[PDB]
């Protein structure tokens, strides 16, 4: 219905807003474009589902997230790809691992403070009925 649209438009705007607060943050700059294949050749062999804040944005715009839960799962993938790819054997590794976790935990904290539970519930029921 019209009212379902209203709801997803509202969702999309909230998701853009969150992604961009993540993206302007200095610590998270390295998550704002795809790991470049030509510049990191074996990434693709280890990491099967690549994800970064730019492709999250396109996905919002192509209406791929009907819930916040689905959006969070993609932010979580950004983090876990990074923990999975990066060895954990020194301070640079340590820096990047800490930023991935920070990204993930910052996304949760923002959603948690700002997302009305009745709004997400309504998003979930609309998806469950499709």
Image: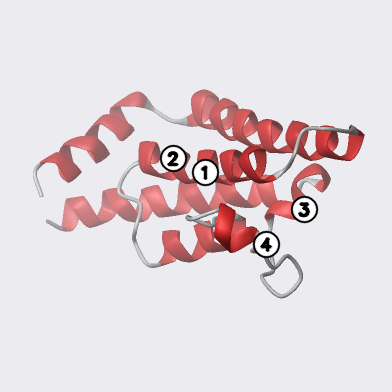
For marks 3 and 2, give the CA distance: 20 Å
Q: Where is residue 120 in the image (x, y as percent from the top left)?
A: 32, 33
Measure the alpha-carbon separation of dots 1 and 2: 6 Å
For mark 2, give the secondary structure.
helix
Alpha carbons under labels 1 and 4: distance apart? 13 Å
Of labels 1 and 3, earlier in sequence is 3
Name the one closer to the observer, 104 or 98: 98
Q: In this view, does 10 lie to the left or right of 20?
A: left
Q: Nearer the viewer, mark 1 or mark 2?
A: 1
Name the residue that disc number 4 marks: 35
Earlier residue among tags 3 and 2: 3
From the viewer's side, name the closer residue of 113 and 124.
Answer: 124
Q: Name the residue beneath numbered marker 3.
A: 29
- Quadrant for residue 50, please give it: bottom right
Nearest-to-viewer mark from 4 and 3: 4
- Relative height, residue 117 to residue 88 (above, below): above
Residue pictured at 18% horizontal, 44% vertical = 127
Left or right of 16? Residue 66 is left
User: Image point 44% across, 31% down: which residue?
Assistant: 115
| Image height of 123 relative to 30, above or below | above
Which residue is tagged 2?
A: 73
Residue for badge 1: 77
């Amino acid at each position: 219905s019209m009212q379902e649209e209203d709801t997803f438009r509202e969702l999309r705007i909230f998701l853009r807003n969150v992604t961009h607060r993540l993206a302007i943050d200095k610590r998270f700059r390295v998550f704002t474009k795809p790991v470049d294949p030509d510049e990191v050749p074996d990434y693709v062999t280890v990491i099967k589902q690549p994800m970064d804040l730019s492709s999250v944005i396109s996905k919002i715009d192509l209406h791929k997230y009907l819930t916040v839960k689905d959006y969070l799962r993609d932010i979580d993938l950004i983090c876990s790809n990074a923990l999975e790819y990066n060895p954990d054997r020194d301070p640079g590794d340590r820096l990047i691992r800490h930023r991935a976790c920070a990204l993930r935990d910052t996304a949760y904290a923002i959603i948690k403070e700002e997302l009305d539970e009745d709004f997400e519930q309504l998003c979930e029921e609309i998806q469950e009925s499709r």
